[PDB]
Image 1: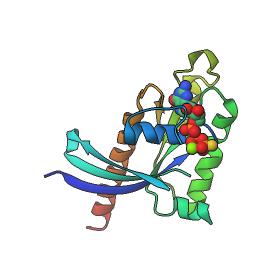
Image 2: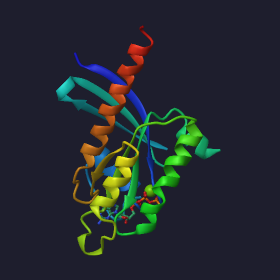
Image 3: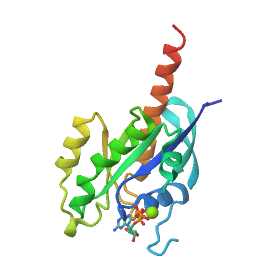
Image 4: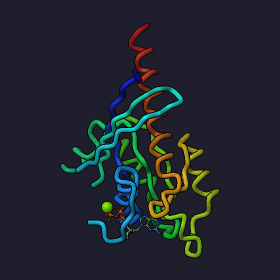
Length: 170
Ligand SMILES: Nc1nc2c(ncn2[C@@H]2O[C@H](COP(=O)(O)OP(=O)(O)OP(O)(O)=S)[C@@H](O)[C@H]2O)c(=O)[nH]1
Ligand SMILES: [Mg+2]
């Protein structure tokens, strides 16, 4: 029997970066330009025999949005530089609301739009590296690395759960 884990996570980023489309791709495995507080996804991780149930929040209301979150995806649109400049503001808002740091994966979304991309891979890698965040290039449209981004976040939250278990068991 696998180990069981449950986490609330938050989708962060400016308007139209693809927060909803990424969540739809992850939970319902499709994409629709005309697709109209949280989604649920159950995910198995074979390498450690662990089962994760996720609450993926995507939206006073701000404080309830962040409360109880154990992780998040920090998205920007590689075709719009302003959305990349603002990811620091989203990180600060989350950490300030929670009054603590939570793991974040930096997600450079819409990488299928090669002809209109303005934020280079190395820029996102450097920001994530400066914050000890993982970095993922994703496309909700093609599905590229979408499941990987959530899976990597799950593994980090699991290792942090294990860290806390050991701290409480000295
Ligand atoms: N080409 C391409 N288009 C994408 C991708 N992800 C989202 N889009 C498109 O970009 C637009 C915005 O995506 P959306 O999911 O609504 O972002 P959002 O962050 O949820 O936007 P908001 O509701 O917070 S304002 C939509 O038209 C969607 O179809 C992607 O990976 N590749
Ligand atoms: Mg949305």
